[PDB]
Length: 95
Length: 192
Image (cartoon, rainbow over all chains, first blue to last red; front, top):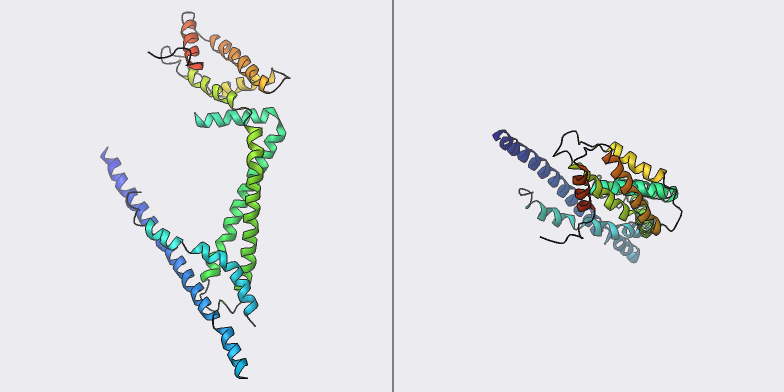
C-alpha cells in the first residue's frame, strides 16, 4: 500500500537524523579527548624540565607517571574511534 | 525452529541434573552483571578525558582516573578468566542432550501440518510440553546417559504416536504414520 511507502520514507528520515546526531556527538567527545590528552602531554613534557632549569640556575612526576600508567591503555583505546566514525558516517544512508 | 531447540535443550539440562543448571544460570547472570558494570566503569572515560578540559595535570581527577582505570583493567582480566572458566565447563555438561532436542524439535513441526487436510486437527504447544514433561517423569532410566538418550527418544515416540492417534479418524492413521516416518528419518528413502 502507498501508506507503507510514505511510512517507509518518514521512518527513514527519522532514523537517519537521530543517527547523524549521535555520531556527531561521538566524534565531538572523541575530538575533545584527543585535544585534552595531547595538551596535557605537551604541558607535562616541559614542566619538570622548567623546574629542573630553575634548580640548575639556582613534584608532579609521580602523579604524571601514575596518570600515564592508565593513559597507555586509555589513549590507545580512545584513538581509533575518530577514524572509525569518520568512515562509518559515509555508510549511513544505505544502512 | 532454532528457538524451540534451545528451549527443549534447557528443559533437558534442567531435568538431567540441577547442579549444572544452577551453575549455568549463575555464571551467565554474573557475566551479564559484570558486563553492565564494566560498561558503567568505562562510561567515566569521557569525564576523565574532557570533564572540564583544563588543569588535568593539576587536579586529582587524573588521580581518581588512575584508580578507575585500574578497576577497569582488573574487571577486564577477571572477565577474561571467567569467560575461559565457563566455556568448556558448560559445553561438556550442556552438549549431552542436544541429539534428543533436535528430533524433539522435528516432531512438533511434523504434527503441526495435520490440520490442512481435516479441520480440528489443531494441536497446541502447552500440552506438547506437558508430554515432554511426561517423558521424564515416567521414565526412571538408570544406565549410561549415552545409552539413555536413545532410550528416551524411543519412549517419547511411543507417547507422541499414542497421544495423536487418540484424536484421529480411522481412515487417517496410515496417513499420519507415513508422514511421521517421512518426518523422522528422511534418509531411508533416497531421492526421486
